[PDB]
Image: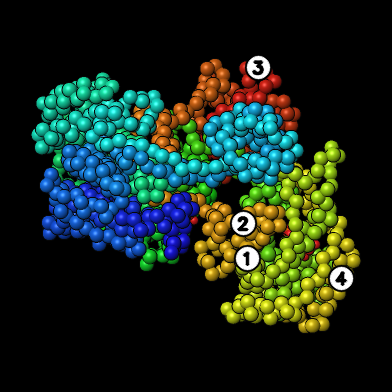
Amino acid sequence: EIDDALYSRQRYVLGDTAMQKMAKSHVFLSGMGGLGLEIAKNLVLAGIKAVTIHDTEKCQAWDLGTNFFLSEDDVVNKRNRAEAVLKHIAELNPYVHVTSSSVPFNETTDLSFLDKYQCVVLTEMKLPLQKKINDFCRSQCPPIKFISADVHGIWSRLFCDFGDEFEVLDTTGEEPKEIFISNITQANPGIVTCLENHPHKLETGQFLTFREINGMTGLNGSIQQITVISPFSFSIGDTTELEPYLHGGIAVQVKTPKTVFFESLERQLKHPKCLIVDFSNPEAPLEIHTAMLALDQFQEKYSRKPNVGCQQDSEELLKLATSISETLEEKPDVNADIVHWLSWTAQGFLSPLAAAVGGVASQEVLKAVTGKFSPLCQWLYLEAADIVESLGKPECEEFLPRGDRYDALRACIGDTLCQKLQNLNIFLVGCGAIGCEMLKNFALLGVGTSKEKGMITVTDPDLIEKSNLNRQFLFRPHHIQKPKSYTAADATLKINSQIKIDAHLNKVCPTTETIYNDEFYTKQDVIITALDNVEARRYVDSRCLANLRPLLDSGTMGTKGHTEVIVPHLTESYNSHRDPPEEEIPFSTLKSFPAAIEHTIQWARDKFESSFSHKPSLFNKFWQTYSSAEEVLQKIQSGHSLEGCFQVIKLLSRRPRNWSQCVELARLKFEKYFNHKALQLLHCFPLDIRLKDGSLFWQSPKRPPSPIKFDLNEPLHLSFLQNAAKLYATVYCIPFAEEDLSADALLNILSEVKIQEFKPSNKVVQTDETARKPDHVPISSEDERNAIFQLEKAILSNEATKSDLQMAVLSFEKDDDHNGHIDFITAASNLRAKMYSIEPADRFKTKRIAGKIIPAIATTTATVSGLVALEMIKVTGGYPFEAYKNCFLNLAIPIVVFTETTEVRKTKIRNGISFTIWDRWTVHGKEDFTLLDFINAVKEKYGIEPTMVVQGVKMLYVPVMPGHAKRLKLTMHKLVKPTTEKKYVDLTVSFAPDIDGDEDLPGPPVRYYFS
Ligand SMILES: O=P(O)(O)O[C@H]1[C@H](OP(=O)(O)O)[C@@H](OP(=O)(O)O)[C@H](OP(=O)(O)O)[C@@H](OP(=O)(O)O)[C@H]1OP(=O)(O)O
Ligand SMILES: Nc1ncnc2c1ncn2[C@@H]1O[C@H](COP(=O)(O)OP(=O)(O)OP(=O)(O)O)[C@@H](O)[C@H]1O
């Protein structure tokens, strides 16, 4: 049913149940403006079963600046907008069935037909009809989920209503957590101690279940409500009547579906529940709602939007707002600034804000149709007032329409900023879904369309994949395996033929820094990143800091996302921020003492790596190095020691010669992994073995394993052996057919297979946590002689040909299901889980964890893209510091967090002289200029005498070190030995602290010029 090859990322987000719920459901969408178009695109990407778009308007030239499917031909033909776009929308997802309608909505229009839709979304509608439709929807049985959203210039309104009661199945959709129990007290209420340095991160009132408790078997399977006492403690209710705590136990999070209560739209006017996006001005959203209501009343009164530059319109609107505020529950003070700006820009349309609101509202429709997350209750008022705020007091000439496609945007931000936008030269790194949305935004904004200066540069090396069609909407299935940037630029050309773009198929890295040299950065104005990993982000941040250019970064996963802004001399840089690295699983944990399913899947993954990539490559490279097995035999006979040769030889002795031999090898490997390991470990540690403190060695987090009895009939075992045999045949270049995987043939083979008996040994076990993988074990001469015997055996059997010395080397593909990599990893991890009494995991979760595939969804991408576009608008405007806003959000709650960005910090070194990360010093001079002259020039220009000198690793001068103090006589070029290609050289200096003996305070990097 569910096309994982298409849906896998969002499948990791919402869950297969959600997909089977967007299936069988039907949604009605009306308005088909820019906002409605965004909704429709987001939903069809998401894969809702069927969508009915509605629009009665005719095509206009004004619609072209906000619609990326309309063309001038459609306006010429005066077609219906929905009719024109219907063909293009269906291209995004053929699985969805899409219909169009144009029945005008009015007072006499009957709404009974709407019952076929479980959710209704309205855009570009007059308010009383919205009231009527909301009433009809919420009066239905079941009530139709109602969503309204509007955009007016820089202002936007979003509203939601799912009826008076709505059941949210999953509140926020995270993985439930598990915490090992350190101790439980017998008290009323009993208090449970978590494992030390493992905080539970829970909430008072949350519900937990328990299992494996030694002592309290009764609460194993019980559910209690907690009351957080400490990060490692909380009360769980009375335990006095119970047994003493012995040991063990694990508490597990319990999810409970909840009920959320909405209100009718008309009633919500007086008492609007408003989500907060900036806690510094919590009352502002109420002001925004008041202003929008005043605009609605204005449109009711005059059948038109207020006109820019009309002082009478602004006065009337302010009067209306003041009258309306008196009718409000709280009666907030009317903000004249908001009213003035709305009157100035009511008729405009700002595309990025519309895109962001569209993404958010679409995610709300997903919430409505699935119950997967807590919905909005009930209002949202996003805005970009800061953009026009920096404009001071402009006039209408900037915003007067000029007959072009950009008239809506011009009415928003004025023509001069449009000119600047068309003249921008933008470098975009990475062209993922975020990149595609940025391209769409630029095309809508006309960025770079100016032939004078405009140029959009983008680069990305990866090819298009079917799995990327879900989010990277610019592409089509016939674009698979083609360069991403090329197809993206081609598609963007369709959106805006005036645009100018240059695509590259290159990864951004220090190796490619030659092409992306500092001059190339100098030509650019802005840098936008749609990267996936952090290291590339830090490298790009270093390049941006070197070239002193603004940089915008964003990252998304699941419903969570964030946007961050860097401005020279204004903000801190990404590398300034630092975090602890990702947690490395302990070597003893992953090798011998797993405790979580993640440990087992990790073990499966690296065992797969060793068995199919690493070891075969070692074998092949070894035989590339050494010509013949007889040569190796001669060398070993003459006492030669070749690193890892012994493993190569043992590999040779293990080479199967037919499919049945591969099957036998797989069976033996199964035995070794899941039977012999447990037996060996238990021989080393019986369940009754105890520590010196008298406690049992086997306790949490350690888990005593058990050998697994082989079973041909087990489907898990069948899949495991099948994938193993397939992989081994692939590596050893042994052909086969699918009938070889039949249980009949496998049973036939295994009837002859004899299993060698287990033999316990006494290998040293790195049971300690701190232990890590050591060096190679010194192979005894007995093992060497055994290998020699096997070697001459192979030589006599003539098994020394080039084919014997060559084998296939694989790579971990995850998207192709037929290679069986995912199947093998799943089988191995599940089997290892049963060894340690751990519940198995499904295939999709296994693929997610092993491949480290980040869950993603189109709505979050669109929203973060809109935010990034707004911030790029601000930085291109050269706005003051306060305008720029870092933002973090989580659609699950949902929650939006705006904040002022991190201000750059200034560090004083001496005499009040302070500098920043942005600052770099420069000097000029001559060849015969000396180091002492350099010190003097520094003390002159910057009022401070250098105390130590280093150029990279060339540790140049310190007064205290004897042999280098005399270098002050030497000139620069003979001393540092620079590369003459440059006219200069860069250097790092620090200054002795005001209190001597402390560390020298480092200054900014300084570049000295030879001339
Ligand atoms: O070399 P690795 O892939 O890291 O794994 C090795 C390997 O097992 P595989 O053969 O299945 O890869 C060893 O066997 P050889 O390659 O040397 O034949 C085996 O040693 P034994 O054959 O003596 O069991 C050893 O087990 P250990 O490290 O416990 O001695 C095991 O390590 P892991 O299974 O933990 O990776
Ligand atoms: N150093 C780099 N230079 C150029 N492009 C890069 C670099 N690092 C990452 N990218 C690009 O960043 C993009 C990130 O977008 P996205 O998450 O859609 O990637 P993906 O590989 O298609 O997806 P997935 O991570 O789900 O496999 C990738 O398409 C990748 O090509």
| Left or right relative to 520: residue 750 | right
Q: x, y (%) of residue 613? A: 65, 64
Distance, label 1 to label 4, CA atoms, is 36 Å
Q: Residue at x 66, y 35 (%)?
A: 194
Viewer-closest of 32 and 930:
32
What kind of residue is marked 1?
A: Leu
Q: Quadrant of ligand 1?
A: bottom right
Q: Residue at x 55, y 42 (%)?
A: 254
Circle 2 sits in a helix, a strand or a loop, which is it? loop
**Coloration mode:** rainbow
Distance, label 2 to label 4, CA atoms, is 40 Å
Q: What residue is pinned by disc 3?
A: 995
Q: What residue is pinned by disc 4?
A: 786
Label 4 residue near ligand 1, CB within 8 Å: no
Circle 3 sits in a helix, a strand or a loop, which is it? loop
Q: What residue is pinned by disc 1?
A: 716
Viewer-closest of 628 and 199:
199
Q: Are marks 2 and 1 in contact (CB under 8 Å)?
A: yes
Alpha-carbon neighbours of circle 4 within 10 Å: few (<14), some, or many (≥20)? few
Q: What residue is pinned by disc 2?
A: 840
Circle 4 sits in a helix, a strand or a loop, which is it? helix
Alpha-carbon neighbours of circle 3 within 10 Å: few (<14), some, or many (≥20)? few
Distance, label 4 to label 3, CA atoms, is 69 Å
In front: label 3 or label 2: 2
What kind of residue is marked 3?
A: Ile
What kind of residue is marked 4?
A: Asn
Q: Are marks 4 and 3 in contact (CB under 8 Å)?
A: no
Q: Are marks 2 and 4 in contact (CB under 8 Å)?
A: no
